[PDB]
Image (spheres, coloured by chain):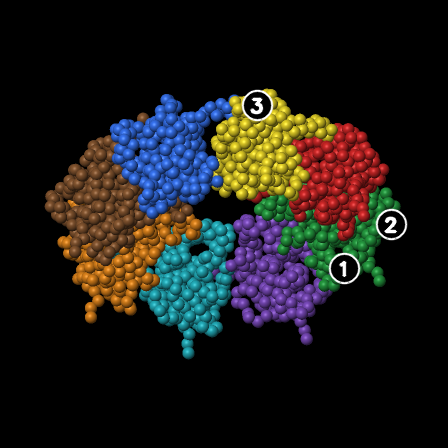
Chain colours: A brown, B blue, C yellow, D red, E green, F purple, G cyan, H orange
């Protein structure tokens, strides 16, 4: 039928894996870090480590780990233009890994237009449909932002809201249908809310550290997370 | 005639069966819990047990109950993406039931667009029409939440409010015609008011317990109900 | 001609009968209760006995009485969905009458859409045109309410007001032309005013009793009415 | 020429006849009561005797009166649905007249839509044209009340205000052309102002008596009139 | 050419005559009373003698007088419906003149619609074009008033202003081209200002008398006029 | 080329002639009075002598004057309907001139619609083109006043303001091309500002005398002018 | 290519010359006075010498001077109509030059319509394209002003702003492409800002003198300029 | 695939070269000055050295520099019309460079309309595509300023804001694809924000020196930079 059974679904869910953040405490919040068949969001301040984490994950997501997770090829659609292979080859070190590999290991794609963006989304599917199980993370940073551009003033939001969810929906059907992990950043019942299943909010704790809280995500803990950042990606904050 | 006689109608109502909430003092508010041939609603806070209640009944309605109610299949349409089979196999225990069974006792289907959500409903009918007396519940959680989305800013409500009831009615016709019990959750003269024949508002009384009140329903008691939430779904709150 | 004479009309009016309410004092207000060739309205509070009275009348209207009134077959178009044959078979007792009969005696019809509603109205005529004098009461509860739904925001009332009176008028032509009694409930120079020839307003007098006053109806008495309600329909309040 | 001479016109006016109000001090305000070839209006409160006055004249205008006025047939168009023949046979007595007669002396016709109301008027002319000197009065109560209805909210008045006078003129042309006396009741530079040549405002002076004043009419007296209301219609108020 | 010379025009102006008002002092204001090739206006209070004067002039304008003025046939287009041949035959007495003549002497025309009105205006020309020098006064009372009717709310004045001046202009071309006297009444740089060449304003001076001032008219005197009114038209107020 | 040389232009300007105002101290403000090839305007109060000035010049411009100005025909376009030849024959005296002459020295033409007003102007050109050097003045009083009229409420100015200059330019082209002196009166960056090259504002200094000031014109003196008004038109104010 | 090199451009710029103002100090501000391949603007007060300077420049621009500038034929498109050959033949004296020459030396063109204006602009090019190096100054006074006319109220600025810059741009392509000097006057990031490369503002310093400051122009000095005006154009203010 | 690999991408970035600002403490803010494959912006006051900086770099980017940067051709698109080659030959000195060379090292092109400005950009690409590695910079000053112009009042921004990014993207694609360094100046979530990857805000610290800060850019230092402006372009500010 147009839909399956409960057992049959619980059959699928046995594939829900988590890509780590390198910040154990942080991972604890997401009960293991980034999740699959789910879009994770990055709420941040003008200067936030999200664009930093993205790189991290560009690699945590290549290192087999927790709950028998393999690791794999990733897709980094960049709108902002903050992608830094250099930052990558730098992280692959904290995890002692071949550089050319880590890079050979990610798939880069710069977004320019609110149309170009989905031009890519609808493509990503294709590369996911060809061969699956190779690609474990579809990281788009940032999604909105480029949409806050090709709008037609505070008067044509009617096209923005409509157009946005036109793919932000198509983005869900990728996540749970092809089974992957979609990390997304931005700065906003807001359409891009029920859309993203897990919403992480970020605040700075004085340069070194940062505090990641949950705005809204199934089984959301009231407690906060204390993670640190370095050249080697995101990591736990020590004494 | 395009309508029946009061007697003939009473004929149909002898089939009106209640599906336990799991919390006796809750079932009393509904005089037996969730009722058939009627859209019931879930009025809850940011963090409400409805999401849990929804699974619970994915079970309760399999356990023969009062009124000589056999127990049957179920159709769960998830908009919010919070259906956790893993939670079901967890409750069947408190009811000493086969795990694989219960999970075969449920039909899952994720809703993505305010159009997909109906694309489904217009199909839920068919499966129901194809064969009857098998499916005893059609639970849609949550129903509105997806419509708040696809809308065209607060300027095209005229399309959403019209589209909304365009299906909400379709829901009713199913409910009473095919005779089931449709449970629906949300957080909102409102079109989705006359829509759902019974409406339950839920408030949390300090973590462990919950207070489910009746917003507006036939023969509505002033008194409130006190139920608790546990892995084994919902149940009464003892000393 | 397109219209008759005065005598000739006074000829017709000799058929204006009243269906009782079981509440003598109440009946006194309506100078005999519900009238014919006239639409009666029910102004009420959130919790009003109108939906209660409706059932009562489902039977008072089958019991020959006052001013040589026979009694007969009724039509209960329900929008809200509060129809309870059970409440009927319960009232038929206060009047010592065959149950299966009372039920066999009413014609049920659930309204779903503002269109469905009139789909029914324009039908009712047909069943009235076929054979008359059998049907003495066309009870619609509630009329508006379902219309306050398929509207297009506070901006398209232009279709509501227009559509409403498009049939609320057609509802008059049924009442006086086919000679019957149309009881209607709702909660609002309002179009549905001159439309309904008799308007009764209802207030509660502490659980047991209720006070029915007149908002506007030919020969309207300033005094109030004190009626009580029980399983056996509406009745006079005793000491 | 498309208009006559002053002399020739004076020719027609020798026919201008007054139809008693029943209350001499009222007739004086109208110098003989209701006047021919002129639309007169009824300005009353929530509970006003106009409704009664309307019947009264259904009689008065059958009783030969001053100015050698014979007395004639009548056309009563009821929008408000308050025409009670039973009330007529009641007054003919105070005038010692055959009951069946009076009631054969009146032509009844209920108005339902703001369109039906004219559908009629455009026919009232015909019956008048067919044969003349027979019908001495065309009473329409009330006229506006039905137009307030079919309108499209306060946003389409432009259609009602235009439609309104589209007939109100038709009324005038009848009045003066066919020579009758058209009486009309209501509760409102107003289009229905220049429309009705005479306007009477009525106020109740403690139940029994009533004060009918002149809002605006040719040769209008400051003094007021004091008439009483009784089963025998309207009449003077004695000591 | 499309226009003449000055001498040639001064040739025409030797025909500018004045129809009296019977109120010498008043006539002094208008330097002889009503003028020709000029539209005179009547500014008044709710109860003003304008509709009274009109009748007067219906006759002053038949009595040869001042500046070798003959007298003649008149046209009284009435919108309001206050025309009273009876009042005429009454004035013809103050001037000792055959009654049937005075009447035989005026041409009556009732205006009903803002269209009907000009239907008449454009006709009047025709009767003026056929034979001239017979008709010395075209009296329209009141002009506006009927226009304040067929408007489409305070929103379609765009048709009123435009339509009004569409003929109020055509009214000028009658006045100066056919050489006559156009007296007009109403109650309002207002379009109907530059339009009417002479504007008289009226105020009451305690029942009997009235004070006529000039709002704006070539060579307008600051002083006021004191005229009286009786059955015999307007006349000078004595000691 | 579609424009001439400065020398060639100076050629034309040697013809620029002034037409006396009649009041020497007024002529000085205009350095000789009304000037050729330039639209001059009349800024006056409710009661201003412009209307008089207009006639005056209908003469002055026939009386050979300074600058060896011969004197010529004239075209008077009256919107306001205040042209009184009788006034002209009155002034020619103060200038000892043939009456019949002066009045043959003027061309009259009444303007009715804002369209007629131009219908004319577009003809004034022709008569001018047909033969030249004959007409030395084109006086239009008043020009705006007629446009305030035909407009569509303050909501269609966009048509009037556009239509306005659509002719006002046509006026200019005449002025300078055909070389005349166009005088225009009114009571209003304003389109009719750059329009008229010279603008004169007039104020009355206690009946007898008048103060004409310059609102805005080439080489404008601060000092004011004091002229008097008399039957003999305008002239200086002696001791 | 569609554009040249830097050297190649610096090749052209060796033709940038300045037409003097006769006011050395003023010329110092513009580093030599009016510049070429650049539109200069005149910001002024109600009574400003701009229309005075224009004439001056009509001649300074014919007198070989500074930085080996020849002198030449000019184009004076006048909208306002303040052109005075007389003022010219007067200035040619301060510079001891043949009169008929100075005049024979300028090309006059009066602007009437916002369309006529550009009709001319697009023409000027043509006369510049035929033969160049003869015409050194295209003086338009004033540009805007006539545009503030053919607008369609404060609502159609959408055509004004658009239309204005449609040629004000075409005006740049004349200036730098054909190498000339365009002086423009008016009284207003305003479109006509970046448009005009040099903006001079003018204030009066008590009749005789005037102070010219810079609103915005490359290398704009904070200091002010003190120039005087006489019949002989603009000149330096002495002791 | 329509996008490359992270490794392959790192391949391209090894080419990212910085082009000196001339002020070492300025270059540090940009870690080497203006950066390749990125739109940098100039945030300045009314009087800012950007205009100068723009020329400077017309040189700097010809002088072999750090990162073994050779030095190349340049494309200068001037909207503001302030490009002064004369200024270039002036700086090459401080860098001991051939004058004719430098000026052959630059490609000039003036932008007139918001359409011309792109007409160009869409060509800048071609020349770039035709042959590569030759042009090392595409400087457009200023970019927005021309768009503020052609717009349709604040009511058609919807066209400008859309048109704006319609090219601003085109700019980006060039930048990173053809690998250059595009510098752009202006005075304004803003579409031209995500547009330019780096943004520099400039403030003047008392004539001689200037403070260039970073509004928002990757790895942005809090500290500010202090550079001076001189004929020799921009450079450091010594004791």
Image-based side of C16 in relation to A48, left or right? right
The residue wearing badge 3 is C127
Q: Secondary structure at mark 2?
A: helix
| Marks 2/1: CA–CA distance | 26 Å
- Select label 2 or label 1 by which is in front: 1
Image-based side of F74 in relation to C161, left or right? right
Whether residue C154 appears in this view of the structure is: yes
Relative to residue B101, is residue F154 depicted above or below?
below
The residue wearing badge 1 is E205
Q: Position of residue A9 (x, y in %)?
A: 27, 31
Single out the residue that lies furthest toward the top: C130
Relative to residue G33, is residue B177 depicted above or below?
above
Q: Position of residue G87 (x, y in %)?
A: 48, 66
In the image, what residue occupies the spot 34% across and 53% down?
A: H144
The residue wearing badge 2 is E93
In the image, what residue occupies the spot 22% across and 34% down?
A: A14
Whether residue G11 appears in this view of the structure is: no
Relative to residue D1, is residue F180 depicted above or below?
below
- Select label 3 or label 1 by which is in front: 3
In the image, what residue occupies the spot 26% across and 58% down?
A: H214
Q: The residue marked by circle 2 belongs to what chain? A: E
| Marks 3/1: CA–CA distance | 72 Å
Instruction: Find residue D180 and report its image quarter.
Output: top right
- Select label 3 or label 2 by which is in front: 3
Dot 2 or dot 1: first in sequence order is 2
Q: Nearer the viewer, residue F51 or G223?
A: G223
Q: Position of residue E73 (x, y in %)?
A: 80, 45
Q: The residue marked by circle 3 belongs to what chain? A: C
């Amino acid at each position: 039928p147009g839909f399956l059974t409960a057992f049959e679904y619980s059959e699928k869910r046995k594939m829900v894996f988590h890509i780590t953040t390198g910040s154990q405490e942080f991972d604890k919040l997401l009960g293991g870090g980034i999740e699959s068949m789910a879009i994770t969001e990055a709420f941040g301040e003008f200067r936030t480590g999200k664009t930093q984490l993205s790189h991290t994950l560009c690699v945590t997501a290549q290192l087999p780990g927790a709950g028998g997770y393999p690791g794999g090829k990733i897709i980094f659609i960049d709108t902002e233009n903050t992608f830094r292979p250099d930052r990558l080859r730098d992280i692959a070190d904290r995890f002692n890994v071949d550089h050319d590999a880590v890079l050979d290991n990610v798939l880069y794609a710069r977004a320019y237009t609110s149309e170009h963006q989905v031009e890519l989304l609808d493509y990503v599917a294709a590369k996911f449909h060809e061969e699956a199980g190779i690609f474990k993370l579809l990281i788009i940073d940032s999604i909105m932002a480029l949409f806050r551009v090709d709008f037609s003033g505070r008067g044509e939001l009617a096209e923005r809201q409509q157009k946005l969810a036109q793919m932000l929906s198509r983005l869900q059907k990728i996540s749970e249908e092809y089974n992957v992990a979609v990390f997304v950043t931005n700065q906003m019942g807001h359409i891009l809310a029920h859309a993203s299943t897990t919403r992480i909010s970020l605040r700075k704790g004085r340069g070194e550290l940062r505090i990641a809280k949950i705005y809204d995500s199934p089984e959301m803990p009231e407690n906060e997370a204390t993670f640190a950042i370095t050249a080697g990606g995101i990591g736990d904050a020590k004494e």
